[PDB]
Length: 129
Ligand SMILES: CC(=O)N[C@@H]1[C@@H](O)[C@H](O)[C@@H](CO)O[C@@H]1O
Ligand SMILES: [Cl-]
Ligand SMILES: [Cl-]
Ligand SMILES: [Cl-]
Ligand SMILES: [Cl-]
Ligand code: NA
Picture 1: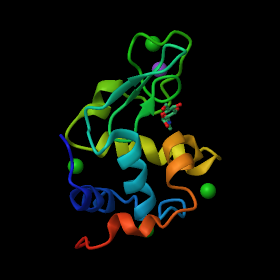
Picture 2: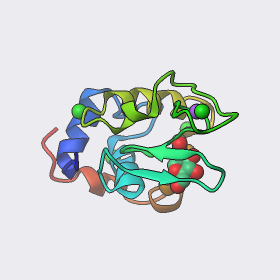
Picture 3: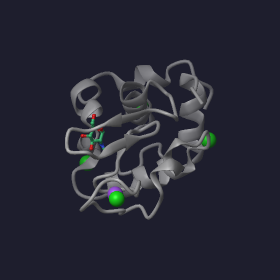
Picture 4: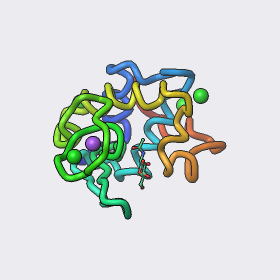
């Protein structure tokens, strides 16, 4: 599923991401925009053999199991395919654990490089929330 911008902001807000660990909703929508272009089916292979999955590009090195990342963890206790569903519950729940692990949203490389320090409120501008 390719979410619309305001459609994804609503779903993130319903699942409790707005100001989760102090990150306003616009941060999460910006992160999704540059990680997956709002596409729940996005995948990308990392150089070390791990793979990032879904709308927030969550990495199999630490957070999910895909059966093909030897030595990795499954800290969110989910198959990585659950992160590709049109329902974003799994991605949001796992995002909440990642963002709580000490490093905030710096765990998302695209957020650090393309959202951090910008007007992230622009990303929820005009949305009925
Ligand atoms: C929280 C998380 O899994 N972030 C990943 C990061 O691990 C990975 O290096 C990158 C590759 O582009 O995508 C995402 O930002
Ligand atoms: Cl915001
Ligand atoms: Cl594995
Ligand atoms: Cl959803
Ligand atoms: Cl933080
Ligand atoms: Na894993």
